[PDB]
Amino acid sequence: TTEIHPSCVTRQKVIGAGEFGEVYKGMLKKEVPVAIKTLKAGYTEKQRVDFLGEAGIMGQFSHHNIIRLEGVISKYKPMMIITEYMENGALDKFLREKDGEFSVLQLVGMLRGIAAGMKYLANMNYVHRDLAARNILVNSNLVCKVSDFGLSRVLEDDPEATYTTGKIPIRWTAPEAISYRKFTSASDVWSFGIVMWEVMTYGERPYWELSNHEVMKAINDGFRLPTPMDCPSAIYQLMMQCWQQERARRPKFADIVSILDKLIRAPDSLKTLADFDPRVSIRLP
Ligand SMILES: Cc1cccc(Cl)c1NC(=O)c1cnc(Nc2cc(N3CCOCC3)cc(N3CCOCC3)c2)s1
Image: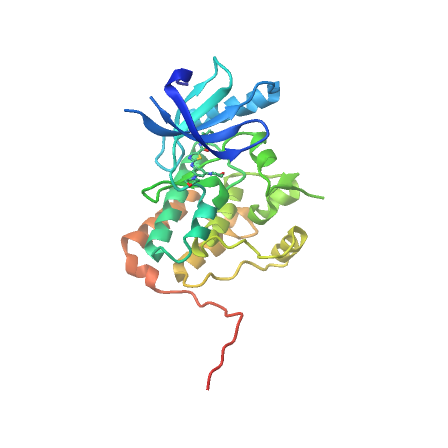
């Protein structure tokens, strides 16, 4: 991994904070904007392994839809991981703050980028385990990149991941991963279907206020999230197939990328909408 000297790094603004380090926006020696994650002195061996392990995993990847690693500071303290800076932050928050501001075509293009990143990861034999809009970042070209890499650190550090009766983010997780700890690229496909629903709804919370146990029971009884408003039928047809109980029946990421690319290349295909089930009746004479 590229080792960066600390005199090349200027931390400008804290953008994320944790107990054991913070995430900063800063500049890297003209100088270029970067994001900087630190690990404070006193860290344990496991914290060091997890922290540098994230940088080790990201250094093995070179794709447009995967956050790019610039380098690390490991010879000085605090240790740091330096990556490209994504100017619009996390996708879930971004969509909630930009409700209704994009075209259907722009939304579908976000999903194609996420899918192409996930296709790369799956083909690299990397199972993400925590695919969700909160773990995708967005830049000033609207490009979405998969973020949040590691081993045990990924689900450990995610506040949405809860201890079940394994520590997992239930509303995003496929049934076999909940039931018996089977995390594969096909469980990431289920997650991706939830991310398709998050994007098309501008960041609605999956299953709204149902509790985690209620979500598991609904999924096991066969219920699935309803169509978003203004959602192309083909998009809904795709997210439903990501949510097949039988893992072998789900599309692979290659199928998902192929379908999305064909829809974008014939954008009239996105004008056919799935019916939306209204929850409110308004009657006027
Ligand atoms: C530095 C680093 C080390 C290991 C792994 C990674 Cl993926 C990274 N890189 C990064 O975390 C980031 C790269 N670009 C970033 N942009 C960014 C930019 C922003 N902002 C964008 C401008 O408006 C203020 C917030 C927020 C965030 N957040 C803050 C809350 O936690 C979720 C992300 C993130 S963070």
